[PDB]
Image (cartoon, coloured by chain):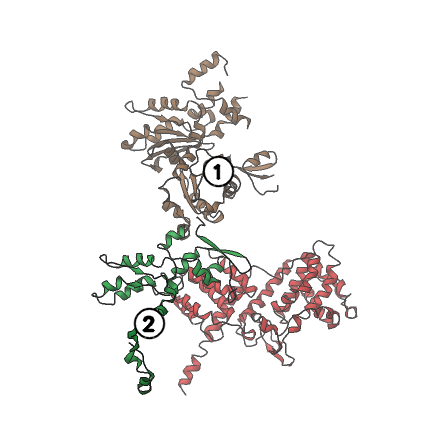
Chain colours: A red, B green, C brown
Amino acid sequence: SYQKIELSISLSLDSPKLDESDFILLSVKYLEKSLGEFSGFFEDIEKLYFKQNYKEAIEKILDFCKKNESLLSEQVVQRLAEVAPRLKSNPKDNESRRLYETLYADHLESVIKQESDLSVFNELRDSYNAVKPEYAVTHETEIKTLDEAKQFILSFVMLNDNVELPLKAQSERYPKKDRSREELGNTPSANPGIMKPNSPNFTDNLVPVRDVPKIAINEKVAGGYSKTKPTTPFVASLSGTTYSLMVVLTDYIEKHKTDKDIEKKVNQIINLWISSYIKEGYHSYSEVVDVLTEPFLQSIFDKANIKLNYGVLDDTHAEFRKAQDYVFGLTIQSAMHHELQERFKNKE
Amino acid sequence: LMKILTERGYSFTTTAEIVRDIKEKLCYVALDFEQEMATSSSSLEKSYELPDGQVITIGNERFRCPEALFQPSFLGMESCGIHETTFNSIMKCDVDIRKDLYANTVLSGGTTMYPGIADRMQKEITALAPSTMKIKIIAPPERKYSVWIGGSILASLSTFQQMWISKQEYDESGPSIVHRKCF
Amino acid sequence: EEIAALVIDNGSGMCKAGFAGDDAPRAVFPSIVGRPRGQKDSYVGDEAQSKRGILTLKYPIEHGIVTNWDDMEKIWHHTFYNELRVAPEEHPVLLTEAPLNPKANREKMTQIMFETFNTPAMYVAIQAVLSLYASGRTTGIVMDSGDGVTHTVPIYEGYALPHAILRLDLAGRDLTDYLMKILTEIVRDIKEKLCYVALDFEQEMATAASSSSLNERFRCPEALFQPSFLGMESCGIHETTFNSIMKCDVDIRKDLYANTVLSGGTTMYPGIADRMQKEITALAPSTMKIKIIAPPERKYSVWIGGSILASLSTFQQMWISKQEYDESGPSIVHRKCF
């Protein structure tokens, strides 16, 4: 009966690890199903999930719920209304976001895979080799596939703190990373963006047993990023090596501002960096995005008139839905997690 | 009001980015919400100044805020409003004393300084009431501080000098002299 | 200050538009859309004919039935936005329909109106009925001859009779292009400043041989009465009218005759009233008394009728509000208009 899918959320909305994110994801399903013209709302709230504006959208959702309380029920609005005021997020336990983002990257890749001319990356080489020649890349005359484009683009770690330092200093934000200097180690795991190794994955979303790092959040750095931006899934820092993409790119912007397609070609790169870095576990959308979105690093784009779409796809639906499903189950099986941690306590 | 203006477009995110001034300088209670909702005219719009000089405009919201009182489903509630609560009570009382209670419904509180809260309830209690009834909803103009005014009066009375719980009395019985002297 | 209402008569070739209560149609423009074979993906109406040379022109309403609504949205967009200078959302809308419209066309007109144009309310009306109201009768028969179709609708007590509406696709467009053949848009215009219908044709032709005070003035309009002229298996507009009247029961025919109004653009030919008289009364029972009423404002009679309708105290209830569409879907027209 359907009233077991409704109770299920009445019961999934009562877990002690529910946060701001999971609410938006479960509610929509709840609205999408309690109802069955309201197409825009699941896109308006969606756009906001990719931007981490869970704050306003929770409320708009709970404004639609009341306005359309007619086609919904007293119970859904009651419950939904009780849970919202009491909401916070923890990077460590914000894991639905992580699935979304892990799945989003693979989505931004086909896109880039559908973006044919990969010559854009090849030309970028001539700019790296002039930034750190001592560490010059000397590879395929042509980067033909994104896997080739990706590995090299991930090779900017060769550009040391030395050629990037002029840039890292002026940021006010970078001095505020909160990655502790305690080398906690490596832990083996089943999915990369969802670094949590004990996360309930779907067997479909399972990758090989790769060894992921454990990173700690130094809560005491005054101004920790995690403190200022808690929605961002796991962040102990801000993307340092992004400062390096910029060197290779500052030299490129100025050499190919002459070309008229640079607007496209710069987003092809920035988007790829954003995707591969989220898939491979190195960072989070926002860790990378907040750096390039800096007063000093945006000037370069302004001078040559480039408008960046920092990897923002407006068809993020499949990813949304897939996550709505995550929480659904995660929440039920972790609420009985204590039904049998209470029935058992009735044997002793 | 803050919700309904943010929705209009004017936002008040912070402790006070002023809506109380709007609540008591602009808002009013209708006799009929529907008539006033239909009134195309932009004539029921009053505008005001933010601190810096940014003037914003409120209309429609002028008469919905005071109505939450008569139709609290707006705010998500199921208690029925001021109009009928007054009757529900006048009807859990004796048939014999209700002639008096109906002709003496006196509004008090700063939440009744809304212009129009007298006649709406006149309409709404004259309808529900029996038809042979005589009614007079009384809204004294000094209602904002009436509870206090009613106290000066009592204390200005030569006869209210016997009704005071003295300490002498308190030390003996305790705090339960109040149930015996103050009813 | 109440919002004026908009009355839009979407004619087969020309469109006539305006506000509520106006004596004469404010906006009249060709109801056509063309695009190049000002970079417009839409050139609607008159500017398209400026570029008759460059454009691929399309006629949206063919025989009263709306074939292209992508362009028809454009005519409405143009009408409100560029020729009526009103914001659609601020004004109530009345639209005119042909007799025998299929259902969907009724439903689609609603969709376009409540979504794309954000109209406050909408109502759909039959052209023929509307035409009768201008002349002041709620019972009768109106023959409307457009640039597209000629429709004969019998109405009783305000209600059209669906069983007896008879449609004929003969119209101004048809009547020209025949004038070409006989006179061998220069032509459509000549067809109007010169032609007339003749009481006794074979008599009128005899005058034609006798003198040269010019045979085409009465011949073009006789295409209507005799459609063999254009290869048609149909009848004369006269028999059609008698026929229609002959599918209504006896209790109502007495007044369908005495109330035959002629409406429409192709019915403005001088002398149309006395011809039909001759033809309807002849064929009819002798006992009947018939009156053909061709008001002198017949080209804009549907609009005129619409203007009044929408200026009325009592049409202000039958407005389909947004609430209803949203609660019903596009089927509400059926439940509000009949």
Q: Residue C204, located in which quarter of the rendered image?
A: top left
Three-letter amino acid code at the position of disc 2: Ser
* Residue A39, x across and y down, in percent: 48, 57
Q: Circle 1 marks a residue in which chain?
A: C
In the rendered image, the vertical position of residue C153 relative to residue A21, given as above or below: above
What's the mark number on residue A170? none
Q: Quick one: B60 or C67, which is closer to the camera?
A: B60
Q: Is residue B31 visible?
A: yes
Which residue position is annotated with label 2? B156
Q: Residues within 10 Å of mark 1 (few under 14, many from 20)?
A: many
SS of the residue under disc 1: strand
Q: Which residue is mark 1?
A: C61
Residue A67: quarter of image = bottom left
Q: CA distance from mark 2 to mark 1?
A: 87 Å
Residue at image coords 23%, 64% = B98
Question: Which residue corresponds to the image point at 35% horizontal and 69% vertical from the top-left?
Answer: B147
Q: Tell me what residue is drawn at x 29 percent, y 74 percent.
A: B158
* Residue C295 % position (x, y): 39, 28
Q: Are marks 2 and 1 in contact (CB under 8 Å)?
A: no
Give the number of callouts. Answer: 2
Instruction: Name the kind of residue labelled 1 in the image.
Output: Ile
> In the image, residue A274 lies at what x, y percent?
64, 65
Quarter that holds the N terminus of chain B: bottom left
Query: Who is closer to the viewer here, A162 or A13?
Result: A162
Position of C324 with respect to A160 (left or right) is left
As drawn, C164 above or below B121 = above
Mark 2 belongs to which subunit? B
Marks 2 and 1: same chain? no
In the rendered view of the protein, which quadrant contains the C terminus of chain B?
A: bottom left
Secondary structure at numbered mark 2: loop
Q: Residue furthest front?
A: B158
